[PDB]
Amino acid sequence: GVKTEQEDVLAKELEDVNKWGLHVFRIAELSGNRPLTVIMHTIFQERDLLKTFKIPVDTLITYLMTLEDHYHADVAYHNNIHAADVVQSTHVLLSTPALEAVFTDLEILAAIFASAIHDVDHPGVSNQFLINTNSELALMYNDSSVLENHHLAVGFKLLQEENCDIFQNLTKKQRQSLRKMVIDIVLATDMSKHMNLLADLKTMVETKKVTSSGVLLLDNYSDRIQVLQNMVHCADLSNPTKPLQLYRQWTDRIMEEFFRQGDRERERGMEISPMCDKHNASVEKSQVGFIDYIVHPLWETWADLVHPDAQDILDTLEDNREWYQSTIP
Ligand SMILES: [Mg+2]
Ligand SMILES: [Zn+2]
């Protein structure tokens, strides 16, 4: 009735589940390539979500293993490890002092479930690639947020497999509200929405109201969903805010995926996508442009929203940017 020795070492790595910089690659190795299942299970137990939503534990495990199996192990970045990392990063952002007791259990479930499914069945190429190749997915979704529409349909469709309906005890009212929030969050992970999300978060920082002692005031769906959308988008673009040991591994994986897309774009004579040309690549310059144009404006605005809970994350991001700028041949 006692853990194996590998399960013990896994359990001791999982004591960091509440911290920015969890060794998620190590958890992936120790769990037998089950990072998403074991991190989701830990978070569901820690936030008491099984008792609150009357989720049978065998149903939760069956769904999570099924969801994890529909991530592609032959994809370097957009796989179950990336899903697990965004879940755990969203878990940490939801615990920020500035957001203490703001969100309902259903909103918390929506943000975590959204994170878990947000990239499921990613084929390791971009929307633009799927549109330009006349792929079946681009035709199903009429070329509009093709991947993000697919991630949602799969995450939901998998609830219908044998003993997978983790929402079986929610009321129709709970399920309709959960589903709308999950759909709103995952569609907001399409980078084509980044500038609009960031504009709305900036507006929200300018007109920021707070409660008695810290803690934001969010008193309408538009505002509550905007913060949840920006939080998961922050978790999705969190790699450059992590310790450099972690960030680097993320950068190696994204560049593998992108160069592999570039190879397919070349070997068929298409325009080679930005950063996808392994012949003409400046990885260090790419990372500095990515931070200066996308990640830093986002995380700086988020840091403003939850002042000063995100100071160390913003500092780590600035250190990594200086590090990458300091290389640049
Ligand atoms: Mg995505
Ligand atoms: Zn993602």
Image (cartoon, rainbow, N blue to C red):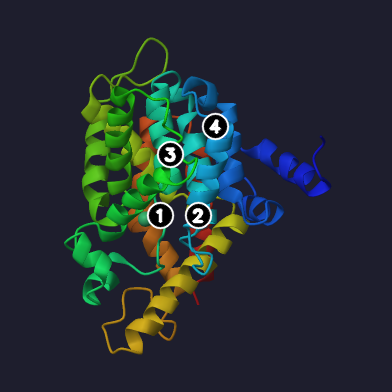
Which residue in the structure is indicated by mark 1? 119
Q: What element carries label 1?
A: loop
For ligand 2, tell me if the residue under mark 1 lies within 8 Å: yes
Q: Does the residue labelled 3 lie within 8 Å of ligand 2?
A: no
Residue 219 is situated, as x and y percent measured from the top left of the image, at 25, 19
**Quadrant including the N terminus:** top right
List the residue tagged with mark 4: 44
Residue 150 shows in the view: yes
Q: Distance between the residues labelled 2 and 3?
A: 14 Å
Residue at 54% from the left image edge and 32% from the top image edge? 44
**What residue is drawn where x is 54% and y is 43%?**
62
x, y (%) of residue 157?
36, 48
**Mark 1: amino acid:** Asp
Residue behind mark 2 = 82
Judge depth for marks 2 and 4 and give the one in front: 4
Name which residue lies at 42% across and 63% down. 288
Depth check, front residue: 129 or 224: 129
The extreme top residue here reads: 212
Crowd band around label 1 with a 10 angstrom C-alpha radius: few (<14), some (14–19), many (20+): many
- Mark 1 or 2 closer to N-term? 2
Element carrying mark 3: helix
Dot placed on the residue nearer the N-terminal end, 4 or 1: 4
Image depth: mark 2 or mark 3 in front: 3
Mark 3 lies on residue = 113
Work out whether mark 4 precedes mark 3 in sequence or the reverse, and give the earlier one: 4
Frontmost residue, 171 versus 304: 171
Ligand 1's quadrant is bottom left
Is 64 or 48 nearer to us in this picture? Answer: 64
